[PDB]
Amino acid sequence: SLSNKLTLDKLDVKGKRVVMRVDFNVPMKNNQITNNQRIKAAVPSIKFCLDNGAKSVVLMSHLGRPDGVPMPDKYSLEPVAVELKSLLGKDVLFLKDCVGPEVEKACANPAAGSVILLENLRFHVEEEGKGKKAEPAKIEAFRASLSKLGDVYVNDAFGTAHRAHSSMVGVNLPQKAGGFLMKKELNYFAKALESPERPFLAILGGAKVADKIQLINNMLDKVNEMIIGGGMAFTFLKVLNNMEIGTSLFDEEGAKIVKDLMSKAEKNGVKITLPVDFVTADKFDENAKTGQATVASGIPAGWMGLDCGPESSKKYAEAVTRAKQIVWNGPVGVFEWEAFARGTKALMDEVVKATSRGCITIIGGDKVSHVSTGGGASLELLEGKVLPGVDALSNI
């Protein structure tokens, strides 16, 4: 909801220093970024600021969960600065901290047009307001320091909008505006949820049932169809079909409530699509020996299902084909491992094809309508919850 919040499009930034919270919390391997989507997504906001004469843009974010200990050897934002420099065609000055005298001096009056990226906010216990306990006078000093780094604050950190952390809710500046990414994300989910195109399909995958209960319930009140996929589905199939599932994931708490989810699906007229066949593995390994199973065959003892199989992909494809809107959150298989990526890659293929014929296609965690930068924050929007990062924006 941004009708009564200040937004970047109406913020005057000419000759002003902008401190901007972003979600640059990007997947990483051996200090190489493996998905730069979250960095690219902040670009419109940054460039609007530069193009309208900001004196500076100070970007701040966390990365991973270093729990309030400075971990520059493992969870440094420095690779992001390098990546952002390409994206912008502008020098990015990387500061090895995010608060204190040195950072304050670097941000006091930078050369016109400067883009500055601070180090991981979570190197300070005062950001989360807890660590692996915070002191109010320390949290206050942390926040007072971030508040010096610009004249105006912008929150473009949609992916972190569910976290009531100091950089998200604690910044004390007269004007705190929602960025273009904040707006775009909220608009898309608001349209999808309040004015859906129909049939409305949700594809939900993931490992467990018990932590997805509220999500599933809230989705059942809005959708026409739901795919339940990923390791979750083994819980449903053991309960509903007494499928023999081997060593695959089994949610003992979620098993107890599958009856109730299906009851809600039924009274709402929601067609549930579960997988019907599987790619099995002999261990939880990328280079495990692999096989095949169906619901009817069962999964042989000692083996686990790590991807859906080809007939499940035809069934998932039936539901995609009928859809005019799709919201997909969670994997249907362990696609980080190529042997177990076919179900996900096939489903992505159908979803891309649906976008080509006019289907609204929303993915979370240009061949689709909207690739969300929010995993958890979007999961929170889908369960009907408030976003502290949005609430804390200044009102008009």
Image: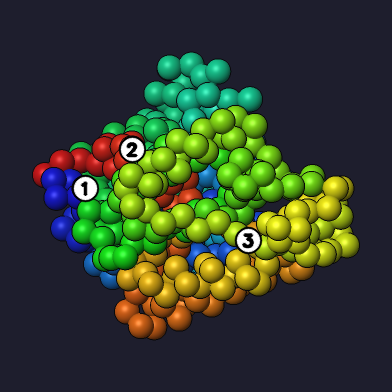
- Give the residue number, with chain letter if any, for mark 3: 276
Q: What element carries label 2?
A: loop
Residue located 37% across and 53% down the image: 270
Q: Which of 299 and 168 is in front in this view?
A: 299
Vertical side of 362 occupied by 153: above or below? above
Graded by Cα atoms within 10 Å as few (under 14), some (14 to 19) or many (20 or more), the crowding at tag 2 reads few
Q: Distance between the Cα atoms at labels 3 and 2?
A: 33 Å
On the image, the x and y values in percent for residue 217 come to 39, 41
Which of the 4 image quadrants contains residue 30? bottom right
Q: How far apart are marks 3 and 1 (CA)?
A: 40 Å
The residue to which callout 1 is attached is: 1
Q: Which residue lies furthest to the left in this view?
A: 396
Provide residue 131's location: percent of width, then percent of height: 58, 25
Evaluate whether residue 43 shows in this view: no
Question: Looking at the image, do the residues carrying marks 3 and 1 touch, with CB atoms under 8 Å apart?
Answer: no
Identity of the amino acid at label 3? Val
Q: Of circles 1 and 2, which is in front?
A: 2
Badge 1 element:
loop
Question: Residue 357 or 159: which is nearer the viewer?
Answer: 357
Q: Nearer the viewer, residue 244 or 204?
A: 244
Residue 227, position in %: x, y? 49, 57
Q: Residue 385 carries which label?
A: 2
Whole-percent x, y for residue 197 in the image: 26, 66
Residue extending farthest to the bottom is 356
Residue sitting at 43 percent across and 17 percent down? 137
Q: How far apart are marks 1 and 2 (CA)?
A: 12 Å
